[PDB]
Amino acid sequence: PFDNTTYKNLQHHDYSTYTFLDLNLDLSKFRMPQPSSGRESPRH
Amino acid sequence: SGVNNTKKWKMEFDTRERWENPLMGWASTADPLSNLVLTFSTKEDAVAFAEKNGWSYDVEERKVPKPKSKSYGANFSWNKRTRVSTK
């Protein structure tokens, strides 16, 4: 059917302290290899 | 940072004895040229003045700050040490 009377964004009521960073950890395996400036840091 | 006091040539004389006045401790001198400082447009004018007055002199070439290469963008270099850690 079709409904327009309910809020369908209730998942975030169950988010916790580490939700955002846990997802970032999950995403790590999908990323492309980072580019490199060619040195360890601007102080090298 | 002002540079307006570096435009002209100066002539000063060798520093001589200053001693403590026994009464007050003020700085006494027997050098009549202790305060004499002359101003010239060019070192050639200064040398000419010194020569005709019989003074032996030393000439120090003018030091001019060399042109620097400045780039605000270098503060954020992608792979150079010029990148700044703070602003």
Image (cartoon, rainbow, N blue to C red):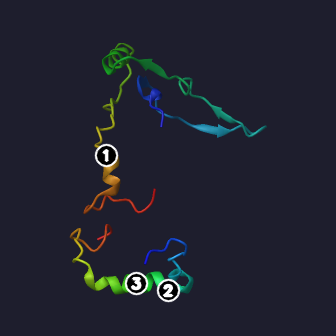
- For this orientation, the residue located farthest to the right is B23
Q: Identify the residue shown where x is 78% and y is 38%.
A: B24
Task: Give the CA distance from mark 1 to mark 2.
Answer: 42 Å
Task: Say which residue label 2 marks.
Answer: A18
The answer to whether one can see residue A16 in this image is no
Q: Chain of mark 1?
A: B
Q: Identify the residue shown where x is 47% and y is 20%.
A: B38
Q: Could you say which quadrant of the image residue A7 lies in? A: bottom right
Task: Say which residue label 3 marks.
Answer: A23
Q: Position of residue A10 (x, y in %)?
A: 53, 80
Q: Please say if B48 is above or below A6.
A: above
Label 1 Cα crowd, 10 Å radius (few <14 / some 14-19 / many 20+): few
Work out whether residue B35 or residue A24 is closer to the camera in this orientation and state it: A24
Q: How many marks?
A: 3
- Precedes in sequence: disc 3 or disc 2: 2
Q: Identify the residue shown where x is 23% and y is 68%.
A: A37
**Apparent side of residue B3 relative to residue A42 in the rendered image (left or right):** right
* Marks 1, 2: nearer the viewer: 2
Residue type at the position of mark 3: Leu
Q: Position of residue B86 (x, y in %)?
A: 45, 60
Q: Are marks 1 and 2 on the same chain?
A: no
Task: Say which residue label 1 marks.
Answer: B71
**Pointer 3 with pointer 2, Cβ within 8 A:** no
For the residue labelled by badge 2, is the local secondary structure a helix, a strand or a loop? loop
Residue type at the position of mark 1: Ser
Task: Give the CA distance from mark 1 to mark 3.
Answer: 41 Å
Work out whether residue B23 or residue B72 is closer to the camera in this orientation and state it: B72
The answer to whether one can see residue A23 in this image is yes
Work out whether residue B37 or residue A38 is closer to the camera in this orientation and state it: A38
Residue type at the position of mark 2: Tyr
For the residue labelled by badge 1, is the local secondary structure a helix, a strand or a loop? loop
